[PDB]
Amino acid sequence: RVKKVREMELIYARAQLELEVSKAQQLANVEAKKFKEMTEALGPGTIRDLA
Amino acid sequence: AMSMAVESTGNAKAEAESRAEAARIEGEGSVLQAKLKAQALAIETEAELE
């Protein structure tokens, strides 16, 4: 019991925690690309001048 | 005196051996009760695993 419940726990735990990191990757990709489009068309020197 | 020795032997001997040889029964009870609960709990747990 303590082996086969707790090892199916390991395998599902994998299937769920590469999952949470996949969520993190995708949400952070959108954050990334939409700061990139933000700054690049806002202006490379505009951000310097405004600050 | 060796008379009262034999009554004392018989009494304490009988009481103690009755308790121990009953503990034999609770022991074999533990033996096959563990054996039965083994597969019983095994099939509950392997039925809740799926």
Image (tube, coloured by chain):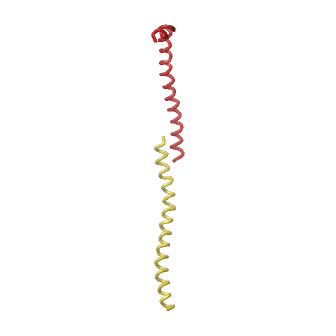
Chain colours: A red, B yellow
Residue ID at (46%, 82%)? B11
Residue ID at (49%, 62%)? B30
Q: Is residue B44 above or below residue B36?
A: above
Spot occupied by residue A7 in the image (x, y as percentages of width and height): 54, 41
**How many numbered marks appear?**
0
Q: Is residue B43 above or below residue A21?
A: below
Q: Say which of B18 and B36 sits in front.
A: B18
Q: Is residue A44 above or below residue B21?
A: above
Spot occupied by residue A51 in the image (x, y as percentages of width and height): 46, 12
Residue ID at (51%, 65%)? B28
Residue ID at (49%, 21%)? A28
Q: Say which of A38 and A43 sits in front.
A: A43
Spot occupied by residue B1 in the image (x, y as percentages of width and height): 49, 92
Spot occupied by residue B21 in the image (x, y as percentages of width and height): 49, 72
